[PDB]
Amino acid sequence: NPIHDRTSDYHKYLKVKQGDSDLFKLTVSDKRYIWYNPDPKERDSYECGEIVSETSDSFTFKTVDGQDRQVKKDDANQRNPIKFDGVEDMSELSYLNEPAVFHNLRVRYNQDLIYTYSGLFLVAVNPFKRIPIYTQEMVDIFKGRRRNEVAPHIFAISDVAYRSMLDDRQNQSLLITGESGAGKTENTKKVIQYLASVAGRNQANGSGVLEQQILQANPILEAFGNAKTTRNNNSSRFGKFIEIQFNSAGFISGASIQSYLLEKSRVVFQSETERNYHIFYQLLAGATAEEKKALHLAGPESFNYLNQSGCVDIKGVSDSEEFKITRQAMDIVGFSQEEQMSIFKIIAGILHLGNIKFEKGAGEGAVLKDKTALNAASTVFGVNPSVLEKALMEPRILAGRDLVAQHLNVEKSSSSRDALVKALYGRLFLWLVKKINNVLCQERKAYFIGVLDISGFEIFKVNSFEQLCINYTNEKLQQFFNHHMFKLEQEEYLKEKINWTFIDFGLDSQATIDLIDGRQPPGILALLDEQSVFPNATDNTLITKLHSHFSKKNAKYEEPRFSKTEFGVTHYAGQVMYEIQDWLEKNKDPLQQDLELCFKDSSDNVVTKLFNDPNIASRAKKGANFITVAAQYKEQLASLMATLETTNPHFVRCIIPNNKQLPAKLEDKVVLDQLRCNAVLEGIRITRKGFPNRIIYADFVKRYYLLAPNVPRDAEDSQKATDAVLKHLNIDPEQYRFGITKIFFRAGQLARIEEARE
Ligand SMILES: Nc1ncnc2c1ncn2[C@@H]1O[C@H](COP(=O)(O)OP(=O)(O)O)[C@@H](O)[C@H]1O
Ligand SMILES: [Mg+2]
């Protein structure tokens, strides 16, 4: 075991770097320290405070500056004994207060260790620097060992999830969730990879066929789904749910993927300094004049879906060659030659529909002084150019009982084409998922290691509809970890030789989970999906009802004191104000109907299958006709949670270092404020509710029995032996609650013997 080998990098990389000695002749003082934040204002940003007299209430001070301010007995965030700093399970801690939490990891992150265990949650802060914790030799270690057995590292979360699958014979699920850019996909990508060797199908070391088939799906799910943004460069327009399929005899079979809402509108809008889908900025470089010609193409700047952005290039990124990498992960999936010209050549239309400009002069009606640019979409789509517009400008619309071709004004006209776009990108993203799925996921399935990555509720300036959705989730998945731990808090509840007094919770987050989704009495998507069908009433009247029902009667809600387009719900993180622009127009999500009418018929096997194959456009039944996008979401959701309500979960709370995207500095502002709102802290403050500090009971008796020369170094049954240092150091029965295998020395008075004397 390289762990023996001191030199073996794993010591310097993932471990605090155990020092030579293990005795009391080491880290030494005898006093007590408390965390104080010197400014009577700014909360975050604490500083070391010294204690002067542990009085009944008035805690005594000596500020780093040397002052004498005095806080109460119950608000002075005290500071953990140093024997501990940079310890793997934050649970081990005897004081869990925001500073005393941000400290134990500031330091470890500081020593180049990014991974620290906390209760269950593997917390990991994002480096931004390239670190060698991923080599095969790495794989080789965390293999077949216990969480405690070896280092805090992602590989552990899985090997564990892995053996587990085949020792209980139930499917499992890893959950990587947290702040944007915060890095889920970098680990989510390294776990699947661990799933590549420990259970790796390769007969001989490496991979065979399914492995790369499965391994180069990503380049794909990225060049089309992923965008650069303000908080990342590999930002994820959607979310995903990949499970890995094995047999009863220990090996991989096929696999899975489950995408959610794309940033479908980003296709047509790139805020300053943010780019459109990555594939767009590749197909224009990694090709030839037999490809630009093959599909009318000018340099990646002439397109008004790419320049309006304010940026194209990516510091340190061969967009040009980044394209090759993705064309091979196609070939491997058996992506055929005709199969790629079509995906792209079908993308290329979406570029052009952009260089098309709706002019206007027939009184008020848009027209086209230039047919050239359409001459391509009609061209590369292989549809009607005359109707393409003729269905564009004057579509037939049913007003009452009559079929009457209208003519949208200079504005509603272009706007309508702008719909024919997400349509290709949604349906096209969609078909790329169906396709992988087909060549990867088998039928005779057995166990699964479900990996889902999707975004924690992050709060922002405008919060359009799309988001009321992705908190709906982090409100649901948040309730889960809340509930699951309760049912597990019954177990150790059965065997300690005494079974504690029934404890209940229920999660008050339930009131809000209704506010959003409730049928009777109805909630946001309920009264929303009601007006989504009347095609006359508008936002103002809608943002007006969500105030009728709730303003002043429903606790978790806040009508805007002033704005008449806002409204505010309150989540597991707190208040959020939402917008009402097109909420109606989008749950509704329409598109003029002579378009599916005219596209349904094409020269393509992939242009046509998207408008003709209901496994693509249609939803399920209800309203009187095809259901609505928020309706779909609510049902498609529980299909998942009720798909974890049978497996063993595995959690990963991801944490970002700074919103500046730079390595080697930890904002004591950003980081500490991803902490307090997310349950990571919260699910262990709860279990502390008794004694947060719990241990294997092999250590304490070796960790402290000489300050009381009564219990030895090698006593065999401390069950009858470690006792002799309690009736001599003197810990009252309330002062702790031990166990018959493990122990948890008092919820509070523990350091009075842990940091001071032998
Ligand atoms: N543990 C890590 N080591 C090195 N780089 C990382 C690590 N975690 C994240 N990154 C980098 O941070 C960037 C953002 O992380 P990412 O995994 O893409 O998060 P997300 O998908 O949530 O936006 C990535 O482009 C990646 O380069
Ligand atoms: Mg991702």
Image (tube, grey):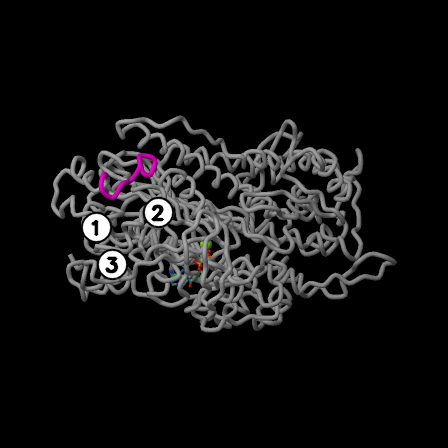
Q: Is residue 506 magenta?
A: no
Of badges 1 and 3, nearer the viewer stands 1
Q: Residue at 24%, 49% (x, y): give it.
A: 198
Sequence-first tag of 3 and 2: 2
Side of 255 where 379 appears, left or right? right
Q: Secondary structure under badge 3?
A: helix
Which residue corresponds to the image point at 45% horizontal and 64% vertical from the top-left?
Answer: 666
Locate residue 170: give its quadrant: top left
Q: Position of residue 347 (x, y in %)?
A: 55, 58
Residue 232 coordinates in the image, percent (x, y): 50, 62
Instruction: State the mark number for residue 707.
Output: 1
Q: Between marks 1 and 2, how big is the CA–CA gap?
A: 25 Å
Q: Nearer the viewer, mark 3 or mark 2?
A: 2
Range covered by the magenta-colored residues: 727-736
Residue 734 colored magenta?
yes
Query: Helix or strand or loop: what does disc 2 sit on?
Result: helix
Residue sitting nearer the eye, 511 or 704: 704
Q: Earlier in the sequence, mark 1 or mark 3?
A: 3
Apparent side of residue 648 relative to residue 45 in the rendered image (left or right):
left
Main SS type for the magenta part? Answer: loop
User: For mark 2, what is the residue?
Assistant: 91
Q: In which quadrant of the rendered view does residue 737 lie?
A: top left
Q: Which mark is residue 138?
A: 3
Secondary structure beneath dot 1 equals loop
Which residue occupies the foreground of this view, 114 or 386? 114
User: Which one is in front, 294 or 682?
Assistant: 682
